[PDB]
Image: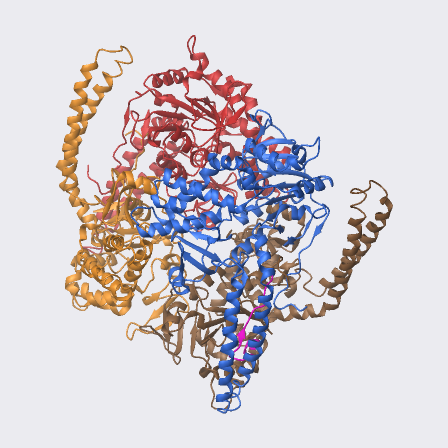
Chain colours: A red, B orange, C blue, D brown
């Protein structure tokens, strides 16, 4: 239910901070992504005068997965490993051959230090990868009509940001709430469960208060009892947090009058209430607590991991919605996984008898097992072909284009690495955590190195 | 015997490149380090006019371990984790308290991007950390007499480099070979074993040919049969390789006349023989092979890992001598490890009955188990104190000052991370690898994520 | 009166933005600096527990000049040239010898890219250089009691920033206005003169509105006629601008109700009124004008010049108060300047007759003018000694410790370079510019290269 | 004849180092550039399989000038000012409109820190800019056939480097010496003149010795007397210097046997003779002199200026061949320059009477000079049109496409800035300097700031 990377004693936590959207309030990711895609697509032709055709682009949710990286320079989308090696790549929607991948990058690795790459985990990655993919396909068709790959990417990023602060996005959903947000009673039960154990919960969102009030009201209030209000659930509600800068920057707080919505500058320490802007530094101080006593839970890293972890110090946990289907798919592939595990053991011992009757014809003899081993080279190619098919069968249980989110080839993917480094704890959704005792001591499993003995 | 991080099919390898010193030719690390320390210490007072006292400094091999990082700015030596968190630190030889560590670094993490840190794995790290430690202790005592911490560090690094190219080091050992180099017959048997399977071996060292000939002659020739010569063992012997630049730079090759030692510039493709300088790019080309068909084995990363792995492409393996005692010590601590593993299981179930009779007095009741649980808080503190002692007993099996080389706290150390990223394969010594069949297929174990099922 | 670096046609300017403090409102720099110094000194011992002695530190305004650079790493203060060469340096208050300067920096140049250097022009540079100087003198005396040079510098910078947002500074002056601010009637006459020609003036300060209203009221209102108000002078008054980020960042605007001081978020284009925060991008857009139609005048570069000039595009001018005494001092040294100019011409022709009767004894003859020229070597040393004294006399007309602000040795100083690159136009004070016709076309003089002919 | 940026006392100089090619030995730049262009063009289609058409590309020497910068990312060539502002730009060979330039760069400035720009002054800049220009014109025509702009640029740079070390270039010229090298007797007379005054001259080239001997023999020997040899002219001749790394790097020296050409490693201090490789650090030391006593003269900055000036310390001078025509053209435009200078003075006083009868109709009156001034607005437009034509006439005296090399618009160009910062002294050719007395004291003219008085 809850996965541990680093120890975190919930008994030592006095405040739990929650991202409002996608963390505290769940959204139908498929609909939400589709919506953002349509708006950004529309906005491209409306303010950037992109080719008419794009309005006709079909949105396929499975065209991308979470954790992908795009290099704005070459209009490519890559799935990297934990150390930045290219597992697979596409130029637009056209896959790049391993051969040509190496000719393109002069290496199997890439350097994310190079800003020409977009490697930040964001809540729109998927939509942005799908639109960008087909967006560079158009570009190729008639280079003279559309800007450059790096220009296109910057444009899409701009539209994606504008629409979020434009009001465009929030309005469409605030009027189709039942379609975009999925309510969950367990969430309010969990918050009450934790508050009941002395925990103080606060939320910080990049959304304005007016819109935040409407949303919390719709997704929390209904599950409350008579005489209860969602406002009593949170010690603080920081709006327009301006994450990630909120964590390591120094932007000032604005006290928000919950009624009229007007604000005043903050003088002195902050007190339970509604604010806008701010920074973790001042907030941790005013609360008179140590950063290791504060736990923040978000849905996306949304920033550079080293600066976030070094320049902040709050314990950080992650909610990874894609985990739902990832786990589900692995449980489904169990029987297939087993059939290849045994088809490997056979290829192993069968390949072992091959080197044996091999380290003879040229280690003790000089010719005698010539035909003896040849029967193994054919019997080994057979057990191999079986494995290729069994692998095809396994992939069918995952995204057909990009495979799993946490795996890149057989090792952990670049995204798996980000979760591991950024999060001490991660789960599918917020309630998975609230299900546990507010005084739980989370322990990580012993990693175990290659030269370690059981 | 041989530890795998990434798959490497020895059947696909046509050339194996070996570092001469510390990889192909083993040295008594204790004596070798002591020697380098004495020379560098002496050189400091001789050319830099450092205080007289240093000549009287006592060398303690256990004062440092491999994988440590020094920040020249503050005269500190730190043991980092895989993600750069400070596990323990010393200012000189004086340990820094966790408290003061955070006050000093404003975080538990550090950023190795910051050049004020020395984080390269080198063959003198240990000696350099010991001398530097006591060297900043002197500095403190009378700040006016010695340069700054960052000045001192640069000076030591200079002496360490000068002595290696000075002739100072090579001469002392070339005259006490039996004391500094440990000969191993298995090494020549292994090389012959691999050559016998079609493998071409070449060596590349940062040492001059004249000195190289003397060393190979002394450590390989004796184990050879009548009519055999060590020169027939190697396809190429690149001298003054100038590693790591040899891998990613473009420095030119100089053909070396094995007799008189004179050189001529290279025109055209290189051929079996003796060279000086060079670069992997030209060498891989002339040999008409793919970089993934070449495997280089070294004893130290000795450079920036990303540039080395990205800008080269040869398969790279590592020989980690410290692995000897590390493994040996873990096997010795096995019984202790078991006694704490059980003393944990008890603290676990005992701590579980604590939250149980806890999530009652404030979840179903309001007061009743007040004294009931208090007996557990005392019984839990006891089973805990036992664990502290059992841990003291365990540490006694490792370096008393810095603990294990591959572990930082309970997770992998910064050095473990370097091995993993830089090496596809690693072992205690070269012969461990030559012991295997030249046509072995090395496979890495499935890593397994926190949300994976067995 | 007004100095031109780059052409700027005031006829093309529709809006002039002014920094409120030090630009629109003049302050007694001596008193203001002294005040900031005392507060920061006091704050060091109050919150950082610095040694008691500092409270007893004497403030000498002439101990520093504008344009100096401090390297936090070594506790040094340097006067650099246009290309970053060290003209003179001090460790604390102790001058460093040219000899030792080179031994310290391994070069006569430094690299400001290196963040260990503080090279930003700020309104407290002088006070900060004086306090820091004596602050590292204390550090030396007893290294164990005070933090490191780089720690000290960061502490001072912190105190300097805290006191500015603390209220500490603004309060002391708001209560001694007649002592800190120097009122000038010409300023209001000039603003009216420009407004009269269609120019729109706006101010943007890093000060809160409440304090801004008090200040403008005190320094502008008195010079106004019956029925006139200072608020009618400005189209916009952006408060807590958060410069320099205001120029290139994206921070949001907050509409400020001039009455109660409360704010609301901005929706749509900004309109004449009072705001807080903001960014030049949105502001330039809403006003429907090109950035080259907007001119901003400040008193300090206060940021990185390339990012400010590249990422903004507004025309930028600078007010350099130190220019007053600099020019005044040069006019005073005129007669001395002339006496050395002639004492040079003599050393020139006299040195020319030296090479003449020199390129003979070894170009036509071989010995004959041996004693003939020796009379010149003594007569040349004399005319030289006279020049050394005449130079001593000249320096007496400038800061005794650091010489001129715009000159470093004989070439332009590092600060001269900053003005030139950042400002198209610069003057001693704001009114110098308002004195000109609002429709003036400012032209820069032809620079002229070494190989150009008159 | 010789232009001074910074003082340099030739009496204090004990060694003068000279680049062999383009500095000591003059080449017909037009032929040399054309040759390099043809070889690189040919090499592109030969090893990179570039489109057949390129072989048919016509080389126009005037298509580029020295000092241009290319941004590999967008396939553009720009002429920058001293502070990096774009004076004019071309995409391939197609000029970019000021309008579109700003839309492309989001600013009038660019940041050369960004490695996507090629801003190093090299001896092939011109040829490379011409070929690259037409090379991206082809790319546009059929994007699918040629690599990307940044790929193309890297390819051209590769061909340009390969051909120089290939032997291709050196061979063609060594066989048409009379066509590519221009011999000058004054050069040998000057060297003898300086040697005669105690100066030691050494040369360092990136060319092999064998080729160097042939060239010096052909360009110096003929002008020598009976019994004289060019080898007696130089104290040291460092071959394959590997500039610029030679200056700041640490590459080792190889002693070269002038006879057979074979080398041996250097042990101890270097002595008069022939070497290969090396570094300025060791060389300055062995000679037992201060870097400020050594003067190096080159033809191109060929590297990063700050690292070259900071990490070396030798006095550096520059030979700028383009200076010939630049000066010549300015002397020719003198009469035109004068006709516009007077046509400006008139537009000035005429524009002054305009603001006068302007600061009345709205400063004293309100309407009266309505038609009075209108006669000036037409009379001012006329004197302006005359100026536009007079400017057209002036440009005709310079490169029609890029204007002057040292001027960008009216201020100094980016290249002028490089010369100024890198060179203390610069001239058209080496003999211009040797013409002066070996004991000359070079002084730079007082720069003079905008607020300085004559």
Question: Do we see residue A119 in this rendering?
Answer: no
The extreme top residue here reads A226
Residue B48 or residue B62, whichever sits in front: B48
Residue range highlighted in magenta? D431-448
Q: How many marks?
A: 0
**Which picture quadrant has residue A152?**
top right
Residue D287 or residue D165, whichever sits in front: D287
Task: Name the side, left or right, on which A257 lies relative to D55.
Answer: left
Please state the horizontal and vertical placement of residue C58, each as a whole percent of the image: 42, 48
**In the picture shown, does residue D166 fall above or below B319?**
below
| Quadrant where the image shows the N terminus of chain A | top left
Please state the horizontal and vertical placement of residue B7, each as a whole percent of the image: 31, 45
Residue D434, magenta (yes or no)? yes
Task: Name the side, left or right, on which D166 lies relative to D329.
Answer: left
**Which picture quadrant has residue D442?**
bottom right
| Quadrant where the image shows the C terminus of chain A | top left
Please state the horizontal and vertical placement of residue A305, each as a whole percent of the image: 40, 38
Residue D57 or residue B11, whichever sits in front: D57
**In the picture shown, does residue C390 fall above or below C426?**
below
**In the picture shown, does residue B285 fall above or below A440?**
below
Residue C308, magenta (yes or no)? no
Q: Main secondary structure of the magenta part?
A: loop
Task: Name the side, left or right, on which C235 lies relative to C375.
Answer: right
Please state the horizontal and vertical placement of residue B36, each as a whole percent of the image: 22, 60
Question: Do we see residue C225 in this rendering?
Answer: yes
Residue C93 or residue C415, whichever sits in front: C93
């Amino acid at each position: 239910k809850v996965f541990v990377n680093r120890i975190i004693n919930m008994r030592k936590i006095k405040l739990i901070g929650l991202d409002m959207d996608h963390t505290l309030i769940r959204y139908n990711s498929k609909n939400f992504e589709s919506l953002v895609y349509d708006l950004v697509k529309e906005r491209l032709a409306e303010s950037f005068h992109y080719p008419e055709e794009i309005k006709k682009f079909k949105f396929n949710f499975d065209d991308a997965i979470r954790g992908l990286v795009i290099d704005s320079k070459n209009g490519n989308i890559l799935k990297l490993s934990r150390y930045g090696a290219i597992r697979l790549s596409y130029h637009g929607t056209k896959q790049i051959s391993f051969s040509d991948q190496k000719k393109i990058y002069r290496s199997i690795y890439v350097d994310l230090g190079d800003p020409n790459y977009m490697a930040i985990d964001t809540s729109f990655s998927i939509a942005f990868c799908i639109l960008y993919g087909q967006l560079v396909d158009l570009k190729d068709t008639n280079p003279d009509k559309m800007p450059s790959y790096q220009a296109i990417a910057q444009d899409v990023q701009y539209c994606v940001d504008k629409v979020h602060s434009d009001g465009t996005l929030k309005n469409i959903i605030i009027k189709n709430l039942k379609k975009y947000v999925i309510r969950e009673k367990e969430v309010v039960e969990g918050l009450k469960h934790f508050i009941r154990y002395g925990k103080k919960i606060f939320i910080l969102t990049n959304s304005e208060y007016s819109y935040s009030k409407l949303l919390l009201d719709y997704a929390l209030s209904p599950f409350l009892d008579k005489g209860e209000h969602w406002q009593g659930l949170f010690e603080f509600v920081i709006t327009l947090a301006n994450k990630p800068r909120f964590f390591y920057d120094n932007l000032r707080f604005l006290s928000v009058n919950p009624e009229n919505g007007t604000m005043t500058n903050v003088h002195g320490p902050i007190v339970p209430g509604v604010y806008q802007g701010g920074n973790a530094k001042k907030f941790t101080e005013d609360l008179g607590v140590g950063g290791d006593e504060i736990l923040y839970i978000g849905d996306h890293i949304y920033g550079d991991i080293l600066r976030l972890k070094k320049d902040c110090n709050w314990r950080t946990a992650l909610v990874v919605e894609e985990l739902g289907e990832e786990i589900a798919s692995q449980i489904r592939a169990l029987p297939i996984e087993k059939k290849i595990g045994e088809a490997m053991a056979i290829k192993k011992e069968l390949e072992q008898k091959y080197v044996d009757l091999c380290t003879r014809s040229i280690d003790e003899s000089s010719q005698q097992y010539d035909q003896e081993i040849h029967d193994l080279q054919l019997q080994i190619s057979t057990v191999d072909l079986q494995i290729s098919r069994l692998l095809q069968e396994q992939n069918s249980f995952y995204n057909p284009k990009w495979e799993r989110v946490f795996r890149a080839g057989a090792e952990e993917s670049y995204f798996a690495y980000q979760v591991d480094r950024f999060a001490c704890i991660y789960m599918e959704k917020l309630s998975d955590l609230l299900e546990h005792s507010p005084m739980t001591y989370f322990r990580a499993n012993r990693r175990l190195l290659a030269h370690d003995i059981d």
